[PDB]
Image (cartoon, rainbow over all chains, first blue to last red; front, side, top):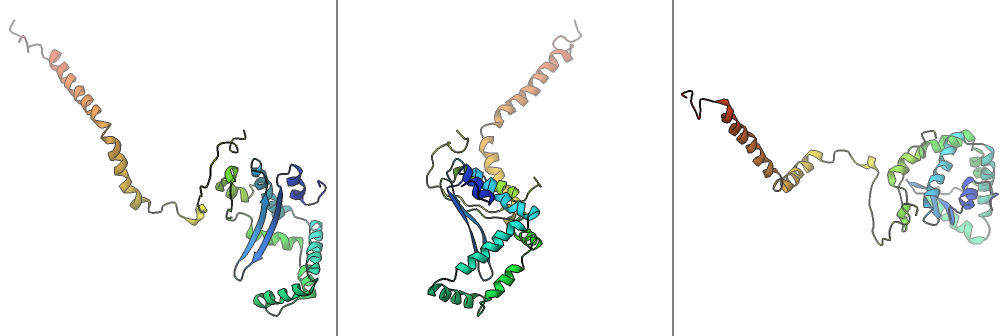
Length: 160
Length: 81
């Protein structure tokens, strides 16, 4: 419904600027991926793209502690619920070994989470977002998709 | 309607492109482009120039044709009578 806290989740639903969307995060050995995956009707596609970006950009400047708490809470809520059932632990071990090796920094996660700060965040996104070079993945009916060079000059604010 | 949405129907085209930073503003500008001069400069030059040449003649042609007509009175009639 419209009462959701997340800015796009409410708004992009408000006009149903999207039928659906999510995000993804995957970090390879030497590499990692950041972004979102979304679905909407074509005539309005422009909307999401316009209104997706700032939800990165406004973070990069104006962001806030309390807004993170829930997310701070969520990820806490997230990883904990990950542990039900026999198999999931089993799968964890394998990647962990292939990834961090032995490490199951269970409580340490929270400590890793307790690390987080408003500055900490506004330091992070400073790296990988503000005025960067994205890549574009799209499939028909792409037609109305804003052209590339917009997106590029659309990534970094002019402060507007 | 919305200018781009309802334009036309198109099927199974694919497009490939890079960031502008990926490349340079002079990918063999000199080397590659300089030949191209000819194929365009030869293309129309068959069709276009010659009419002007005719003009340029007329320019001198009539002028010269003009020139005598006045410039020298002791020509057709010399100053004898």
